[PDB]
Amino acid sequence: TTQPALLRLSDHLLANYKKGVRPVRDWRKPTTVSIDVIMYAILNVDEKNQVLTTYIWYRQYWTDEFLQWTPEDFDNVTKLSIPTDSIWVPDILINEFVDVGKSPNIPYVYVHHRGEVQNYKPLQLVTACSLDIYNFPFDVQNCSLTFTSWLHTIQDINITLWRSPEEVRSDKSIFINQGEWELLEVFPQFKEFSIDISNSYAEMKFYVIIRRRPLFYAVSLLLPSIFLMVVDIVGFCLPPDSGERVSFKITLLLGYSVFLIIVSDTLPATAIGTPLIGVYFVVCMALLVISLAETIFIVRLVHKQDLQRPVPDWLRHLVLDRIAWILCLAVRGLLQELSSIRHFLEKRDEMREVARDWLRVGYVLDRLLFRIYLLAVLAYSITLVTLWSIWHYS
Amino acid sequence: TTQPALLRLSDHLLANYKKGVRPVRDWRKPTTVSIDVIMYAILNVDEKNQVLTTYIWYRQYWTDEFLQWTPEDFDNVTKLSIPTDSIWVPDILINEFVDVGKSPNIPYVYVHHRGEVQNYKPLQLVTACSLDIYNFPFDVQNCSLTFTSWLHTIQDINITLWRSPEEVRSDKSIFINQGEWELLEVFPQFKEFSIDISNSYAEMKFYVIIRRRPLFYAVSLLLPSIFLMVVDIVGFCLPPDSGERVSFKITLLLGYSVFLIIVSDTLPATAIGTPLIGVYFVVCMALLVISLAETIFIVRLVHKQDLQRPVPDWLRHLVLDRIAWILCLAVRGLLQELSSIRHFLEKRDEMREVARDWLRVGYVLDRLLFRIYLLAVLAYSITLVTLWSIWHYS
Amino acid sequence: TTQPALLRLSDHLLANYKKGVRPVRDWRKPTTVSIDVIMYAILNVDEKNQVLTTYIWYRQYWTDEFLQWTPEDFDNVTKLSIPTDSIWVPDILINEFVDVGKSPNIPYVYVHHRGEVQNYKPLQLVTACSLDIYNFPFDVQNCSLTFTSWLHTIQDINITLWRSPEEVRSDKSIFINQGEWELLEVFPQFKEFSIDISNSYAEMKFYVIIRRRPLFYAVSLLLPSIFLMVVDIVGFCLPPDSGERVSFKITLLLGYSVFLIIVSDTLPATAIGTPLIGVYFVVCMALLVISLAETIFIVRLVHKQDLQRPVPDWLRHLVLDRIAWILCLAVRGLLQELSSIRHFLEKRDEMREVARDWLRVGYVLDRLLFRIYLLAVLAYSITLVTLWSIWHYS
Amino acid sequence: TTQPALLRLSDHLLANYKKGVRPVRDWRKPTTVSIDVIMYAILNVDEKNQVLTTYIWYRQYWTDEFLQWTPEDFDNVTKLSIPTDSIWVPDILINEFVDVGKSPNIPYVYVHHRGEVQNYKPLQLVTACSLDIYNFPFDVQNCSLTFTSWLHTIQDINITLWRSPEEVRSDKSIFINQGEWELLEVFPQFKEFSIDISNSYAEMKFYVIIRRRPLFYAVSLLLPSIFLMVVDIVGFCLPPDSGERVSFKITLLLGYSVFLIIVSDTLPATAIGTPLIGVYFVVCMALLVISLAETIFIVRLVHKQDLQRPVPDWLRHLVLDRIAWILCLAVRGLLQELSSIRHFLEKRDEMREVARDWLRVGYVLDRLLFRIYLLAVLAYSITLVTLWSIWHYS
Amino acid sequence: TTQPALLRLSDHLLANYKKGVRPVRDWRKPTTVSIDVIMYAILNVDEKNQVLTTYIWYRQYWTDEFLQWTPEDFDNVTKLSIPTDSIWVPDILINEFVDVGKSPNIPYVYVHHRGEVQNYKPLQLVTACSLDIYNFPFDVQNCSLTFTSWLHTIQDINITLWRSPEEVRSDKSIFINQGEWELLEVFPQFKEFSIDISNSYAEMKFYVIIRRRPLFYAVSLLLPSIFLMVVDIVGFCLPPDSGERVSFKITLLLGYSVFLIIVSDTLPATAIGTPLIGVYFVVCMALLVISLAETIFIVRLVHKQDLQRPVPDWLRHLVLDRIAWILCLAVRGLLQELSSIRHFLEKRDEMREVARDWLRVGYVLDRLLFRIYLLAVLAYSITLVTLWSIWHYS
Ligand SMILES: *[C@@H]1O[C@H](CO)[C@@H](O[C@@H]2O[C@H](CO)[C@@H](O)[C@H](O)[C@H]2NC(C)=O)[C@H](O)[C@H]1NC(C)=O
Ligand SMILES: *[C@@H]1O[C@H](CO)[C@@H](O[C@@H]2O[C@H](CO)[C@@H](O)[C@H](O)[C@H]2NC(C)=O)[C@H](O)[C@H]1NC(C)=O
Ligand SMILES: O=C1c2cccc3c2C(CCC3)CN1[C@H]1CN2CCC1CC2
């Protein structure tokens, strides 16, 4: 021989190698591939369509008895690059595909001098995992990735791991943070399933566990919710007989009904169960309609509508009690004329003294309903805080 | 001979095999493929464009007389992997395509030692089926998938089933739940049609039947609909002569007219027939304009506009009836001066006693219209419930 | 010879067949292709960009003198499948392309024993046709599809029809209904054009004619338009001196100005001419500003602003006419005191009797303007109906 | 020889033709391609991203000395079709690419008997040109297309034009009108640039000039702008002491503040300079806040707040001037009682005569501010018209 | 030999060249590629998904010992074009890929007569860099591009630079301005990293630094923010006892609550930290609720609700102080009748003189709260300006 290059090694291997035949001497021994993954980013989690988008890195290796030389007498060449096309490559796919992601192709593989080839490639994957929105800002997710052969049986292609499974779980090395989702754990599991007798299919399940960072939503839905409670505490200080107190409490009720609709499109509500913040917005209405349905009771109670004098059953029940429970011939002709004038004024006087008494009752009930409304907001806001400190601690 | 591998089998088959010729000995015998499907997910059901998106799995098998060896003397090899490119593959397409979905390709097939090849592949499909939105939250759909050869006639390619058709119907095995659509049944049917004499085309129709889960829409359109009825029950308790009762009933009517428009874009209305909830929102207006068009009648009836005394035809018709039907020289010079003063006061007195009487009539009609409005809402809400319990039961 | 298969026919044809050369014996005889189409669906009609999207089916056939055997002595084989790659295939494209639609490829053709090949393929096409929105819900469209060779001249490739043109026009066989567009007619036409001397290019024009179903828009723009006229008929029943009648007529005018903007994005207005419903919304404003600009005239007319007595020119012109046109020392010291008291009351009396008279005039004009406003709506709504019955009939 | 076909010409050329070598005898003579374009449609002009989308047609031709036969003795064949793959094809790209448009491929070229090949192909292109939004409805644009070789130098590939440049400018032949953009001119220009010594690169610049049709925006932003000026001319006719005049002028000011925001997303504002209609909407506010800030001055001026009598400095300045500038023991015991009654009435009389005088001043200023507001709108609307007639003329 | 062309050079090289083998004589010497980039445009910076889109140009060169001739005796040919397919091409990818951009392919390379090939290609890239929105209109970004081999180790492929790194930093030559992002610097850096022992991977990091032009957002969020402060300065000039002052201050508060929501979707808020303009909108509310919560205090203070006389503790504290701190038998029978009349009038007089005194106090507090509100806006607006002049200067 002569010394052209290392390329006469590359002629020695790929002269009679056939691309399609599965590379083994005896047809009973299965080819054993060995995979490994690393999470890189989490592009999109679509709650409505149950579709999760993920870019990962990937590598795998398998042995074969056709690409096998002796390293001596080929000028000590140990490894080698060979293009991906001219090598038998196994088909390993994800069961949970719903679409084909766009990923770069890598046109080279390694080949060691025992037959061990290696294959690095990245791949974007769009899968379909089941999500739960039972507790919306504070939620973990548990989506699956299932690597399997698509055609070959378990006496044909078998799947193990590159590294130990304890080392895969704590591999948070290149993951992109600052991106709405925090990666916790990548847990592998082997499992064999059979859809029929004498047809077994090996598979390998990776479980990813991600947790949403709740900080983005404590300003987008907590801030306008408590803000339309601090207005109604200001709103009760209007005296009820003015006329704008009814017009005040309907404007912001309109103003909050716009808020429930313009947010609900950006907050998803998928299958069984509603998110638990949706209950905590209905209670925001019941402290707002009851605030509306008591000023209707006072305006009806304090008005000038030629009404009767208030009842002494409910005068000493209210006025003299609640200041200590919580709060604190020509002569007779003109005499006929003058007395008729006084009769036209004294019934004008009588109609105003009656209207003072209901108006006196109407302020005592307004201060009394103002306190228990102030205690209903105060006892509700402390229950909201103590369910936030339990989660935040540990 | 020698013993290189099993690959000398792979050289024995694919040495003179021609890819394009249809593989049969006698040209009169038709090649019979045999298909099978399993639903996996339902990605999108677009009501407006009548387009349905679905990811399924798929397998098929056919015989041929060129790939046929004896298993003895090839070291007992029974099955084999061969790349998909070097084999005649029949063209089986869906008639209802409108676009090409993106699906992974599988580069291998099996070949048994009688000639039976097999072919597993997944495929995303976007079809065009006719949808009905006649009853929007409670609806089944009946979309079709039609597998057929695209070119060959029925004496060239014929289609049967892998499994029995009773086993295909009850195959809900890998379907993704928790996803807006519940799969009920996949029903197969064979049918032969001819577009011309001496040109018959076999086909195979799969019917899918899906049912929408109505739970997502009982919070997005039922809750604000009944909520703007519980405000108007509070709204009638304002006394009509105050002035804000007209301003109250127009604000929420504005507030509901925003609601009909911001929802109608997310609820589709396609061909013939409107959805039956659209009728049940027009009746929500007729209990809201009539609630508006009666407070206009009371405010016109109770006002100070130098009006005449109310008519005794309609005084004893109303006031004395409806409390039992439902509800319950210097002397004469000053005498000229004083009597003229009393005349200026007694007509001031007379104009207020007239205005008390209409004001008395105006409250009796307000309580009477409040009851039959309270019975119109009550008799309408029970009809809404009993049409929900009939569907929910069985 | 021996009897391997029919495949020795497939070796007899494709042994020396050259793919690129146009297949004819004498170079002067033109190759004549023959096309045919069937509409399948109409995916999208974008009015703004003048782009129309359509999925059709398609077939064509041509003769050639190289693929020509005798059916005797090849075991009577009449037709044959040959892959699409190894055959000269003519380039027939649409002139109106603006993009490339995604369509499945069909890898087989037929070949008869005279040389006639056939070629079935479906193809999605996005074209650019000119649309008119002159009458928006009731409109036909006339878009063109032009099949032509892209390179070859008319002495090289010539185009005729498969079927008679009378049979193509009435082929509504597989078209998907229930989809916003109704197909009427597919009309073919042959035409030869030359862009230069000695360079003629054959082409074939198909005209499609589609008609929009107007039912979807009689609920999305007719219903809120007439609904904000039935409120203003209720709106005039408020007495004008109350104070909310000005506040009533501005709220719904705000409420309709929101409606004109939130709809106009979903209703297109392209080149020359506005759609004729846009005129019928401006007239909806002129019956709404004039309804606003007359209650401003009454409130200015009926008010307490120390005004003068109304003019007897316009008292007998109005009050006594329009009830028949349409509607129906100590003594003198106290005498100095008492007469000064009466002078302070009689000018209080005089200022109210003046304010009764304008207030009397103000109600007669309000009933008179209420009738001719009720006749202006009534005479306008019957003109709207009779332009709907002319189109609906025939 | 024999007479198989014209195909022995196609064997004579492509037997030893090598695809990759640049086809010239002497390596010093440059290959000269010659291009030409025709605009077809303008799909999208994205102002925000500075990206312009265009579909054009394209053709080019070049000579080579390898594809060259004598037309005699090959049965007089002058031209020929050859597939695009087996020919050296130059790389001509656009410098302004930002993405790859989707365009059909044409698999054939012509070859004449001197060596001149020809090549027709259409191509969608997305470029990046700089746009100016300095005057939004009335604007021309000047975007560039630069055809150049991407690798070869100017002694390797050189670019000229097919036709004369005067004939290219006035080629508006197949352009799709009725589509928001009117094509004016396509102007070619040759230019040679060098990025380094001894490395020159030929290029060819086409300038397109397009003009927006402004008709679509005279109904989407001119009509609601002048419409909320004809309401405020009606709005001043309310008398100021009524109470709704303040509530009237705030509702439509709210109503126009919604309008500025819901439009500004559909009207772009890119780099340096704001569009000149944005100035003409700020002036629409200054005629609307000043209309608001003068009714605040009148309501403060006309009110009952136990105020003092108006000053005679400003009484004869206003009231007596502006009607000609623009507008036009028992006895004494009862005497103690009666005089005290008159004292309680005469100060009630005095407080109303003071309130008549400010109320008299308040109407004269309201008519005076109504005229100069009516002249400020009138003098502004004529300036708006005369800037529209200058552009519309020529 | 003869003289066919230069093409016998192209036959001399590519006769025995093998495409897949890495082209070096001795397998120990690494192949050294050398890259260079130029920014062209910045298409999109998506803050929410942390994805940045960029179109760049790119070139690289490497040596090999197989493509090497002597320029003498081949008619002095120095360089040459060879198609890209038939040459070993190294795999250089970006680590930060999340998708595959669409870019044109260049089918030619140069080859010099020493072995140096060259390769020009453009490529669109979508990467994933970490963004900070800590200060929203005034922000620089620091995103990375990392060119590396994907498979080969550092004794196999090594990466250096074409030009000096000082020349790459100041290369702003073809960058498209007028496009929301200004390019500052492109800084290169070499770094070697090892993921394992005996496996080192060379890489090359380019840092891009871009700065947002803040001019687009000084009209979209600064202008309506200060505009709803100039209305409330007009808003306090209404006298508080009128009745519309409460209705005025709630309409624009509704009007600004719409503004905070319709803008917050177009302004992103990603990971840790809120943008600093979000603090400067909360302070816009605290100058707006406090403006609301003081007119509630005045309306409660000035009202007719049969209240008591104001306290002389707080009369001389306020009224007599703040004008210098800041602001400036028949006889007795009628005597029984007449004195009873005077008693009915003098308590009518007394109830109005009490209501004058609170009304006098209520105006002095309104002018006093008007000044310190005018100083709170003035002292806040100057702090906003001086934080704009520090950034604008240098
Ligand atoms: C659609 O538009 C074309 C416009 O070209 C119509 O074309 C005319 O068709 C008639 C026959 O119906 C020919 O005699 C004319 O010469 C055509 N016009 C031109 C300019 O060539 C076509 O009829 C239209 N479709 C319908 C249904 O009216
Ligand atoms: C579009 O912009 C180009 C800018 O380069 C204009 O270019 C100039 O064109 C004139 C001839 O019309 C040349 O003499 C100048 O040298 C060009 N300028 C430069 C900087 O090279 C072009 O005219 C513009 N189009 C129109 C219609 O005005
Ligand atoms: O893909 C991978 C990859 C995939 C799976 C497991 C592991 C890796 C590593 C590191 C070891 C663990 C590196 N990498 C890439 C990083 N660099 C770019 C391509 C690889 C080599 C260099």
Image (cartoon, coloured by chain):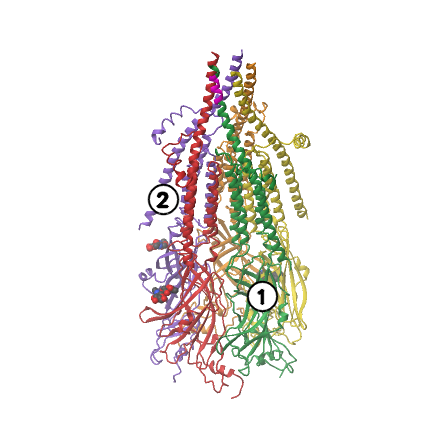
Chain colours: A yellow, B green, C red, D purple, E orange
Kind of element beneath mark 1: strand
Q: Quadrant of residue C147?
A: bottom left
Q: Count all numbered tags in the image, as a single digit.
A: 2
Instruction: Tell me which secondary structure the magenta stretch mostly adopts.
Output: helix
Ligand 2 within 8 angstroms of badge 2 C-beta: no
Image coords of residue D67 (percent x, y): 38, 74
Q: Quadrant of residue B133?
A: bottom right
Q: Amino acid at mark 2?
A: Leu
Q: Residues within 10 Å of mark 1 (few under 14, many from 20)?
A: some
Q: Quadrant of residue A327?
A: top right
Residue B83 vs A50, above or below: the answer is below
Q: Is residue C332 left or right of residue A283?
A: left
Q: Is residue D309 left or right of residue E354?
A: left
Q: Which residues are magenta?
A: B332-340
Q: If the picture is divided into quarters, which one holds ligand 3?
A: bottom right
Q: Amino acid at mark 1?
A: Val
- On the image, numbered disc 2 is attached to which residue? D384
Residue A352 visible, this angle: yes
Kind of element beneath mark 2: helix
Image coords of residue B329 (percent x, y): 46, 14
Residue B309 tag number: none
Residue A234 vs A39, above or below: the answer is above
- On the image, numbered disc 1 is attached to which residue? B208
Image coords of residue D270 (percent x, y): 44, 49
Both labels 2 and 1 in a single chain: no
Q: Nearer the viewer, mark 2 or mark 1?
A: 1
Closest to the observer, A321 or D103: A321
